[PDB]
Image (tube, coloured by chain):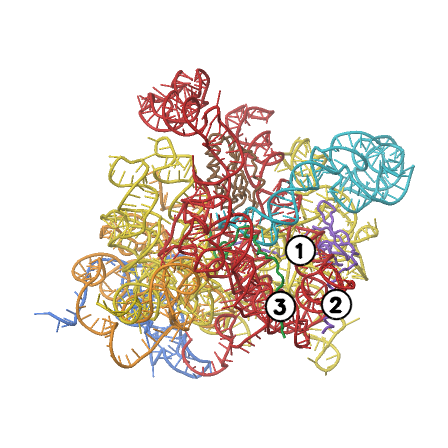
Chain colours: A brown, B purple, C green, D cyan, E red, F blue, G orange, H yellow
Amino acid sequence: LSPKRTRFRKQHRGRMKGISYRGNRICFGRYALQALEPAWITSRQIEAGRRAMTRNARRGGKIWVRIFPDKPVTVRPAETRMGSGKGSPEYWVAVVKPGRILYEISGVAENIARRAVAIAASKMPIRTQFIISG
Amino acid sequence: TKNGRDSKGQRLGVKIYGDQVAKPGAIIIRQRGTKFHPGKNVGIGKDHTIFALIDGLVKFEKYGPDKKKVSVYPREIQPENPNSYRARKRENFRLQREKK
Amino acid sequence: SSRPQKKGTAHHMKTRPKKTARWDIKRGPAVYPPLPPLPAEWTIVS
RNA sequence: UUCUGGUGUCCUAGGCGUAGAGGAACCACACCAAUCCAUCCCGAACUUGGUGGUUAAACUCUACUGCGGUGACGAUACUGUAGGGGAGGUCCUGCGGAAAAAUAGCUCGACGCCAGG
RNA sequence: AACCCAGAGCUAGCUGGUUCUCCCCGAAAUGCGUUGAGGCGCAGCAGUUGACUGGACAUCUAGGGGUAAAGCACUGUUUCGGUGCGGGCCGCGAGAGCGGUACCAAAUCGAGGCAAACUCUGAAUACUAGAUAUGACCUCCAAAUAACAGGGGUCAAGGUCGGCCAGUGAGACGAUGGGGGAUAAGCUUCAUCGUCGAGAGGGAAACAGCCCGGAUCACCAGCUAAGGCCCCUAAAUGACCGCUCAGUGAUAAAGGAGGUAGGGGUGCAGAGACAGCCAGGAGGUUUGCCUAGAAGCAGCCACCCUUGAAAGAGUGCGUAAUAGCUCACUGAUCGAGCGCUCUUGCGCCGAAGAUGAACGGGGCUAAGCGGUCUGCCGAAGCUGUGGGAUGUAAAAAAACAU
RNA sequence: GACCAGGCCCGGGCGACUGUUUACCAAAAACACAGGUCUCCGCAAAGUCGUAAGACCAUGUAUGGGGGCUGACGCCUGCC
RNA sequence: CUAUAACGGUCCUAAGGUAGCGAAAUUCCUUGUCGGGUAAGUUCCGACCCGCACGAAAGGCGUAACGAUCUGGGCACUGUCUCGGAGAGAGGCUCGGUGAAAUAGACAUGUCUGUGAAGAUGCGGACUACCUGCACCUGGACAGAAAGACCCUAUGAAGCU
RNA sequence: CAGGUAGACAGUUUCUAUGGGGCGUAGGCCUCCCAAAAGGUAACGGAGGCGUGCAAAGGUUUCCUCGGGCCGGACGGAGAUUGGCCCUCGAGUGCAAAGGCAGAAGGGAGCUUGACUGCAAGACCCACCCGUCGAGCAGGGACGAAAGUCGGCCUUAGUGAUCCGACGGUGCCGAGUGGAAGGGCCGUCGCUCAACGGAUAAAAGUUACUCUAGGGAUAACAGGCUGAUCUUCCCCAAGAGUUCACAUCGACGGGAAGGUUUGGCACCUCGAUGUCGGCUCUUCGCCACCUGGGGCUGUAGUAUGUUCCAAGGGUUGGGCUGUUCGCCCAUUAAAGCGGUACGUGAGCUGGGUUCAGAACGUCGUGAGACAGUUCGGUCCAUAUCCGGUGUGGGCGUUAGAG
């Protein structure tokens, strides 16, 4: 959602790169949501997907939110554009590159996790798929 | 309303790299603190800069886990010279000042 | 919306003729066998 | 001519730990007293002068990869040039260079001087 | 704050303008400073005259780094599990020993992630230097002809320090590396490079910056680069494999799809595999709670066994509830392929603007899109044949570079 | 009977009013005004123009002469 | 009972606005809310006072008469209008005389669409147009004027404080 | 002659980067990042400090290791002072950060004044000015027994050129000569000259009464790029709808198109592209208000709700306001939204880029001012060409005609 302490208030951007070879594996959970598409995912889509698959499981099992934002995005107001004064308490952002696991789920059967992970992939600006723990 | 634009312009760095001919009094390293400790045939400065004492090459070698040791060696090397373009340059200076 | 139209010299890096067929880049000019040199263009006759 | 022990220098830095050994000689602790000296108090430290026993502590030697340090090859990311795709974020080719991490290993240092017996 | 005359041809860091020719060379839009920002002084980069010089371009080697990548060893930050310093309340009445606890939290371990102001690491390039290496041409030459090498001659090119003497100091786009923005702008600011500026020609329909390419001049000469070969408009209605049926062929996505051409997996069949018709789909049973009824069909809890060829406390409809229609499953007739997932290639929809085909045009199922094979067209490039000028150079001729 | 020759009423704002004002885009709510108040001035006055002589004031003498503000008239004009 | 403040304390000043007025030539929110007028009224009038930011000679509140003053409403009246129509003159049109002007690089001077210094008769593709007058209309020629009064720059000028 | 003293009067100043402004902010020095692994490098990019302080916190000799957790000790507890182990550089360095520094550059003790004079080979930085380091020599010393070390501080910030003036001192000049007045030279002092390369020792505002030289380098109106904002549509479905995601809405989110609002850039135009509303008169788009056809409906019929095709045609009269928009009345099949530079002022008229006069509130000491209000306030024009509507004349239509 949002980090409590910030070492630095405002932080500039950074560009996406190739396939994340570290966060591609499955640590916990049986099923996952691997992203094929490098972009930003705010904490707002993470709340949307989290409510989506928690209320789409709704009887048993547990999900695993992998990513945390850890960088802010400063939106300048409509004040005729010259400075980056204050935009730090505005929306946070997680960098996602291809390969990276976004969500995981366990305790759920086959097609209930297919609709749980697949319906909650519609709350997201980047194309994904669901991955079994091989 | 910005609280910025406080640049500094100050410069430092390695002045004379390794395997290079030094001079007596030539400033080898300008550094902040001691990235390069004074070895032999060198001297440390008032603001920890490393100058050479004698002529010759400079070298770098460890004496701990990280340290670097700027040193100076006397360099009695290389008497032979197979250069032949330069003699053609001076010889053509002679031929052009004798032709006209 | 949020899709920028490609203006001038960005239109030229996109819509220039590019021969993106790996065969037609390999083509060198044709080689005929060498011929003996042609004679003199003219000759003094006295 | 090995050990012993003052001395260094290159060092992949060679250490922790578990084990075995050494008091002929050497090194080191221990007991007694304080005159130079000394601790913001103590001869704990330092100094002087002796009983002089031990390896107990400390040093030295030999093993182990249990930690530690070091660390591959192949790959692969990246990147220089020459290009291509995408609406963008950005990706893919030819040639050259080439990681890091991890892993297989390597490492319980190596060369010299001088005085004994 | 009148008008005329005079200072006065005031002053203007501002605007406009500044007139004949030929040849050689040829920028810059950067930094610093400025009562300065559209000015100026200096440096950078020109021209010319020198004096010292011997370098440039390729290849190799050596040095410092801390960028990209990477990583959690420091600084933070963060997801989860366990032991969890410590608290929460029931409680003990009065000078408290230490009791009750599936609940929250410092610390560590494990599995993990992230960071321009984090680094145990660490490239490729770049910078400084060292080192290796004749750049073309003509001619002689070993009894000599080839060739190797050599002798001689000619040309071309780098830099430093000056003298005199200018402009320039508004840049623009394209690739990469980033910051500001909303990783929006033909946006703004930087760092390396290419072009324009100051660059003509060809391709791009037209069109500064994109690709080829560097225009001394002539020819009613030839060969090519980029790009093209149906017609407008030069050259192939060329050849052989596949694909597209949307005129896609100019276009934008999420997502949907028995589109079509494949490719990889997995499951059933000559002891009959798929699709349709027909037969069965029952007993305890209306499992136990509720309701008037809940009989599978408003719902709650599990969600049986038996006959068997198979039947599910039911897949849906329906009824006041039943009854009942029907299906998952099995039996029977003909019979030989049928599923269900990933995946590309080209396609479809998504995809809608205001004057009128508007996407070069006509049009084409190839004249479209991918993979090769041979030729041609195609510039002011190159070559060839001839002039001119500049530099060597100091007379002419000749040569090489321009 | 042609030409000629008042349209009016009901409310409100401002200015009391008749007048004056930007010749050539503003006639007004602007200026002035009668009235009020403060303040200066004893004549060789104050004030104004002029280096000066001097002049207006004024051949007038505080019931008069300047200057500031407000604007008839009616009620008043508070505190510091 | 909901309120609201007769009343109270405190801080700071030199003093904390008196009478009267009050969404006003003053009120941003605001077309405040109510009542009148109107079929319907951001304008008008009468009120409340939450006076952004009235107020007592930079006077405040009133009023008869007055005003080419502003503004609200009503009667009569009519081409203002619905929705135009006819007629008379001076022009305009034609002929004869006299006869300019602003403007003007040369003009063999189409439409769409696209491109381009981002609004093209002039460049590209297509379509459409025999040449050339006369009478009307003015959409374009970024039409004419006139070195933008607004904006900014000038180490400009000037007035005023 | 001297003091005081009125913008009554005179000459002047009143910065710049910027958002091209009231309302702000900054101007000079240092550290990290941006900064793309040499150095450099910009933005009103992200974070901080500095305008000093120390008689030791300088010099030298010598000694020592901190910091944190645990355990012990009726004051004293979690934590003071003391003892012991563990981790070994995480502490500290006058203060911001960076790089350093573990038998230290960190802490203590002794003696101390090199926090000297005269210098200085060579380097770095380099527009210039500057600024930084320095072996080595002489004098005279400090510490140490000596070796050696010391020309301030672990380093980088803690500052300011010049002209002039002042103090201390001197074997210098002394306008005929001897002096003196005065001036040098040396050592230092005096600027928040902080707009910090400093204009002068000394300087604020307004102009709507304005004026000139310029600029599209630079705003407004309009066009262009962008699409944050707005309009429209679509993907998923937790729900609401007696049951029931998808008759109808659809939360949390996501993907597009358009260029009609407000914005961003400043690319054409200021030697002139005339904004807002109304009248007249077009034409065009569909994101459909009605008319025509249809699907679905929680559609019994009437009337619907939503949606598909379809832009041929229509889309009223009025009270308020300058009004666009909007409210209200009477209705109507319905009283659509927009493009065409307000679509349209070389066709026409009011509020306005609120022009010159005046008044109210408020601000200002004042001149004056308000994206506050009110009253009054000149708007030109004979069509050259294209374009249009009408109407001819010539020629052509292959002999000439009706």
Q: Residue at the location (47% across, 30% down)?
A: A59
Could you confirm whether marks 1 and 2 are on the same chain? yes
Q: Look at discs 1 and 2 and give the one toward the viewer.
A: 2
Identify the residue position indicated by label 3 in the image: C40
How packed mark 3 is, by other alpha carbons closer than 10 Å (few <14, some 14-19, many 20 or more), is few
Q: Which mark is residue B12?
A: 1
Query: Vertically, is G74 above or below H161?
Result: above
Which chain hosts label 2? B
How packed mark 1 is, by other alpha carbons closer than 10 Å (few <14, some 14-19, many 20 or more), is few
Q: Secondary structure at mark 1?
A: loop
- Locate residue G112: give its quadrant: bottom left
Q: How many marks?
A: 3
Which chain hosts label 3? C
Query: Vertically, is F21 above or below H388?
Result: below
Q: From the viewer's perspective, tell me whether residue H335 is left or right of residue H227.
A: left
Mark 1 → mark 2, Cα distance in angstroms: 44 Å
Dots 3, 2 in contact, CB < 8 A: no
- Locate residue H155: give its quadrant: bottom right
Could you confirm whether marks 1 and 3 are on the same chain? no
How packed mark 2 is, by other alpha carbons closer than 10 Å (few <14, some 14-19, many 20 or more), is few
- Locate residue G79: give its quadrant: bottom left
Q: Position of residue E170 (x, y in %)?
A: 53, 63
Of residues H5 and C18, the one nearer the viewer is C18
Identify the residue position indicated by label 2 in the image: B91
Q: Look at discs 1 and 3 and give the one toward the viewer.
A: 3
- Three-letter amino acid code at disc 2? Glu
